Length: 208
Ligand SMILES: */C=C\C(=O)N1C[C@@H](n2cc(-c3cccnc3)nn2)[C@H](OCc2ccc(C(F)(F)F)cc2)C1
Image (cartoon, rainbow, N blue to C red):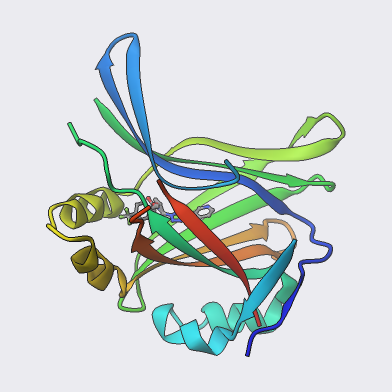
């Protein structure tokens, strides 16, 4: 029973995101493979109660966060990942760009969850840069955690995409972007994953 509606006004917008493997063939030659990406306006809704068991739910958990921060800042992102790359000076990285009309100090928290339990959290703090009339927050070449590198390797070893999808049923990512000074939730993305059989795809929903 979803509702499909505009996003409306938000203090922070996600403009770009990619997760990638860059491999250096030699000092002047590099290959880059994208696993997932966004950015390269009606949204349907998803009942957040459907996903509580896939994320931590203690103090500071998804249910507490949703109850507090503005509800229009919460999204579910379904990714279809591209695993079709020949892994061989490899750098596993993420890039993202956010934009705002306000100058803020932003903290981005990325929690990796397995069977609904947090197994890694990455925390990055970003200051604004003024760029042609607005404030831009760019994360360039943020390294993956060891857990994701190992996880990608293990998935790639499986012989069929449906076996990777079964494994991915219990893997999720929770991104929470907060105003560091005020603790306001600026954006929250609860992320679920399958493997693409198409490159990579995604669909975004509003959490309600
Ligand atoms: C320590 C964490 C880490 O290295 N990660 C977090 C994963 N992540 C980040 C985001 C995200 C979404 C929107 C905005 N900002 C960040 N979503 N997921 C990164 O890995 C992504 C990923 C790569 C490959 C696969 C796989 F295995 F299915 F192919 C899944 C997820 C890195």
